[PDB]
Amino acid sequence: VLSPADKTNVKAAWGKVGAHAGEYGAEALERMFLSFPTTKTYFPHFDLSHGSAQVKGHGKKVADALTNAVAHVDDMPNALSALSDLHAHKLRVDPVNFKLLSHCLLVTLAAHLPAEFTPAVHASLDKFLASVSTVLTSKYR
Amino acid sequence: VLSPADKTNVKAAWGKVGAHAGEYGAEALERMFLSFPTTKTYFPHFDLSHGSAQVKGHGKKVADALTNAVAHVDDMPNALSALSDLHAHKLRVDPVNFKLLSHCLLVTLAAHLPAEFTPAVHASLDKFLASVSTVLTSKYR
Amino acid sequence: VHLTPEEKSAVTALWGKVNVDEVGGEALGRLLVVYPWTQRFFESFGDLSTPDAVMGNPKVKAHGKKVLGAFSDGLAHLDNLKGTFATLSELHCDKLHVDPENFRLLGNVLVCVLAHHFGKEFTPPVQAAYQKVVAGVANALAHKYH
Amino acid sequence: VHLTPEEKSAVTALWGKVNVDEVGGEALGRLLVVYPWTQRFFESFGDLSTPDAVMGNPKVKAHGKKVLGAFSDGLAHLDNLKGTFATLSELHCDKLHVDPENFRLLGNVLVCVLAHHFGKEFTPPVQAAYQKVVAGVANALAHKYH
Ligand code: HEM
Ligand code: HEM
Ligand code: HEM
Ligand code: HEM
Ligand SMILES: O=P(O)(O)O[C@H]1[C@H](OP(=O)(O)O)[C@@H](OP(=O)(O)O)[C@H](OP(=O)(O)O)[C@@H](OP(=O)(O)O)[C@H]1OP(=O)(O)O
């Protein structure tokens, strides 16, 4: 469970993200594809080259989803409810990849926020991203 | 989330696991220790030689914990409150290992209960052991 | 992988007693039942909305046989599982877009199945030996992913 | 682990400019903080009750210099990581009783630390290179477990 400091911690870290959403989210996806190629099996229909339009627009979607989650950190299962549906019924992504992406998100926030990524904020973000993965994978079976 | 069918599949399949709880639990410990030697790192004070009394001893405590969980399948997070406090603050076992043990409990039930280990009961017990582990790792951070 | 002789001995022996037309369909069948998200790659096989639907499905049995056939090829060539499954690795990856994590799940489901088909004969050390085998296989199939 | 020659270059080039005493304390510190259960192996270090307690903790600082220094030794032997860390592998197993999965956790914390420190320089391909490296070190340290 996300402690009080967890929510505050994530709110301040994610805030600093600001309007660099589709940018950070697209970097995280790209970091994930290159570092864990197996995650590419799920985007066969995508143009996965550097800076493609599909990743960009898709990175913006993941980044916004996380921003909504942060604003609803108290009730994530309700806000991500619709998304949990998609990933569980259609996309059918293996739960292992959720960790791979969270890690790539951590690395992007780390590489863009030299000041905001403290050990505590780092610990709180990891927890937060693991809670979002938990929800996105709740309805699998 | 364990559906109604899942709860019945477990209560029903775990019934036979009832008598031999000590033989089954210890066998599942042995299979784990042998199939996945890294798990042994958590029992350095144990005598892990086959047939060991500690393994058999602890084997029954784990099976008896699982019997109790089955009985309180609807009150899983609370029924295991003190067992999760233990794992989280005292034992601090890395969450990946629970998956290893769970697979071994499934192999042990498969080997002993062919009649009851149906594809559906197989699925239900997997979901059951998965949530049991989720509760046991809930207070880690 | 790295199987000792007592291991390659234990494995080959048990495998010989394996029902080539039943164990494969069973492993693949239970994979789709226990990890339903894997049904995604076999929507061309028809009804899979249920345990008796997936299990009793003929394409499931017939394809599971193909899969076990490939596995047999592995329990002979443990010294070089990669070359043996190289081609398949490239297929699953380039044309089939299958997350190699599913190779790990199926390996473990196979162990449950072997345990179910052999009972007490599937002793812990025979299990251990089979854990290395299925790990080796899923690893060799994931080897050409990119 | 297969590091393409340019990955080899990238790894060695980024590492030549790394403050090994600063990165070690930081990585071990953050592992202790982010996955606090890892603290179970260090009740000899003292105060670890708060993020600050950890990161400032001189034992945690000193020890990290040791971990990363050993780590550097591996980077000079990408060709033989198993042999390089074999002695340490036996020690972690027999004497320290450390689950090897903790190695993987640290490898990914070390990546987060390298990104934090290098910023944009830690490009996606540079991360990709280092992901291989940390995985290789982790496998190398787990190699002598039994
Ligand atoms: C950090 C958690 C993640 C979040 C918050 C998330 C969020 C989203 C969102 C918002 C969509 C767009 C839904 C729509 O409007 O159609 C989506 C689509 C998708 N996600 Fe995730 N996702 C995450 C992780 C992953 C991972 C682990 C994978 C697989 C490697 C995955 C695979 C996909 C795929 C295949 C699509 C469909 C892409 C398309 O065809 O447009 N997602 N995800
Ligand atoms: C299926 C999940 C598991 C169950 C339900 C379970 C249950 C138990 C129980 C009941 C205890 C006894 C505590 C007491 O006396 O009150 C225990 C102890 C312990 N568990 Fe678990 N456990 C699980 C998974 C694991 C795993 C994965 C490991 C790691 C390999 C682990 C390591 C231990 C150890 C070290 C002890 C202490 C042994 C001793 O000193 O007697 N447990 N577990
Ligand atoms: C034990 C590991 C596996 C082996 C040895 C294996 C082997 C094979 C083989 C021999 C084929 C035949 C292709 C050909 O004609 O050359 C096949 C096809 C296929 N495999 Fe696998 N496979 C494995 C695991 C998986 C897993 C886990 C999945 C995913 C759930 C999968 C999905 C597929 C699919 C979808 C096909 C296409 C069949 C069709 O729809 O016509 N395989 N596999
Ligand atoms: C990059 C991976 C790692 C490397 C290269 C590494 C290396 C080493 C080195 C050089 C030492 C000192 C040996 C001695 O005292 O003679 C050591 C000690 C130790 N390591 Fe690791 N280690 C790694 C990961 C870890 C992790 C992940 C843990 C567990 C969280 C860990 C726990 C320990 C402990 C407990 C000691 C004994 C410390 C003591 O003196 O009290 N190490 N390790
Ligand atoms: O002797 P090594 O150079 O260490 O290589 C072997 C093996 O290939 P061979 O047995 O054919 O030489 C694989 O090396 P890669 O091709 O992957 O580099 C690898 O197997 P994986 O497919 O599981 O990656 C495995 O170990 P590792 O992968 O951890 O390097 C390792 O085996 P041994 O270390 O047991 O000899």
Image (cartoon, coloured by chain):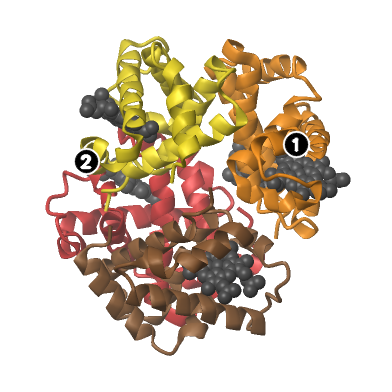
Chain colours: A brown, B yellow, C orange, D red
- The kind of secondary structure element at disc 2 is helix
Question: Picture coordinates of residue C48 (x, y %)?
Answer: 71, 44
Instruction: Please rate how many residues cluster around mark 1, counting C-alpha atoms within 10 Å: few if below 14, some from 14 to 19, many from 20.
Output: few
Judging from the image, mark 1 belongs to the subunit labelled: C
Question: Picture coordinates of residue D65 (x, y %)?
Answer: 29, 58
Q: How far apart are marks 1 and 2 (CA)?
A: 46 Å
Instruction: Please rate how many residues cluster around mark 2, counting C-alpha atoms within 10 Å: few if below 14, some from 14 to 19, many from 20.
Output: some
- The answer to whether C81 is drawn above or below residue D50 in the figure is above
Question: Picture coordinates of residue B45 (x, y %)?
Answer: 27, 23
Residue D128 seen anywhere in this rendered image of the structure: no
Q: Are marks 1 and 2 on the same chain?
A: no
- Kindly identify which residue carries mark 2: B85
Report whether the residue tagged 1 is closer than 8 Å to ligand 5.
yes
Q: Which mark is residue A1?
A: none
| In front of the other: B110 or A42 | B110
Question: Picture coordinates of residue B31 (x, y %)?
Answer: 48, 22
* Image marks 1 and 2: residues in contact by CB distance under 8 Å: no
| In front of the other: C96 or C55 | C55
| In front of the other: A114 or D91 | A114
Residue positioned most to the left: D47
Looking at the rendering, which quadrant does residue C96 occupy? Answer: bottom right
Tell me the amino acid under the disc marked 1: Asn
At a point 55% along the width and 36% down the height, the residue shown is: B123
At a point 46% along the width and 30% down the height, the residue shown is: B8
- The answer to whether B76 is drawn above or below residue A60 in the figure is above
Tell me the amino acid under the disc marked 2: Asp
Judging from the image, mark 2 belongs to the subunit labelled: B
| In front of the other: C68 or D75 | C68
Residue C44 seen anywhere in this rendered image of the structure: yes
- Kindly identify which residue carries mark 1: C80
Mark 1 vs mark 2: in front: 2
